[PDB]
Image (cartoon, coloured by chain):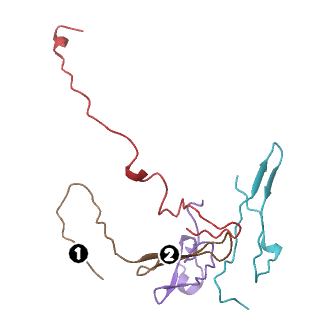
Amino acid sequence: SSETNLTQQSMPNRPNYIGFRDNFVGLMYYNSTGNMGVLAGQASQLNAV
Amino acid sequence: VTTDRSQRLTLRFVPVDREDTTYSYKARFTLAVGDNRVLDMASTYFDIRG
Amino acid sequence: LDMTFEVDPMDEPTLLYLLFEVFDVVRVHQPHRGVIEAVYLRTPFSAGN
Amino acid sequence: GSIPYLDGTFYLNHTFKKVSIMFDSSVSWPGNDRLLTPNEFEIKRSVDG
């Protein structure tokens, strides 16, 4: 606190909106052979994906 | 000797149930020798990750 | 095939995103209960080739 | 040094990641859904789910 510090100016922080992407883009792994999803006939276990 | 058909060489199975305890683990499979095959049990093993 | 894109310079490193358009098709077969057989053919770049 | 092309004395075999074979561009070989999932011989894996 000081006589000069009476003169401080503030500006609002920049707006920033956060949420999930459209259609939940990116929430499930598609097109990754490292993390491939499965839909397989039990009990042959041949993945159809 | 060899078939003209679509048919896998190696099959991988996952448990139909798992039981887990202090001193043991039990895993249960349905092994499935489908039609026009024969399986030598020497060709089988339990593959464990831990 | 050879191609060449003349593009405006940018101070950012950028990517040319080039879609070779194809057919990317699957046929799904279900001969007995619990069995899915699926067969795929991307028709050029067909596939991993 | 040794000339692996003539001497035998190979090394670098461990550098292969995968290979694919394709007749007439569409006839993936051996095909017939033989191998654990593919249309290609996956020699080694950097990540295994």
The outermost residue toward the bottom is B1
Please tell me how many numbered marks the rendered image carries.
2
Task: Tell me the CA gap for discs 2 and 1.
Answer: 33 Å
Instruction: Locate residue D26, reporting x and y percent.
Output: 48, 85
Question: Which chain contains the residue that carries disc 1?
Answer: C
Q: From what the image shows, is residue B5 above or below residue D35?
A: below
Q: Residue B33's image quarter? A: bottom right
User: What label sits on residue C4 in the rendered view?
Assistant: 1
**Residue type highlighted by circle 1:** Thr
Chain C colour in the picture: brown
Chain D colour in the picture: purple
Instruction: Locate residue B41, reporting x and y percent.
Output: 82, 73
Name the residue beneath numbered marker 2. C26
Question: Which chain contains the residue that carries disc 2?
Answer: C
Mark 2 or 1, nearer chain start? 1
Q: Residue A47's image quarter? A: bottom right
Instruction: Locate residue B36, reporting x and y percent.
Output: 76, 83
Q: Which chain is red?
A: A
**Residue type highlighted by circle 2:** Val
Q: Residue at x 55, y 87 (%)?
A: D6
Q: Disc 2 on helix, strand or loop?
A: strand
Q: Residue at x 69, y 74 (%)?
A: B10
Q: Residue at x 83, y 45 (%)?
A: B23
Q: Which chain is cyan?
A: B
Left or right of residue B1: residue A21: left
Instruction: Locate residue C37, reporting x and y percent.
Output: 60, 75
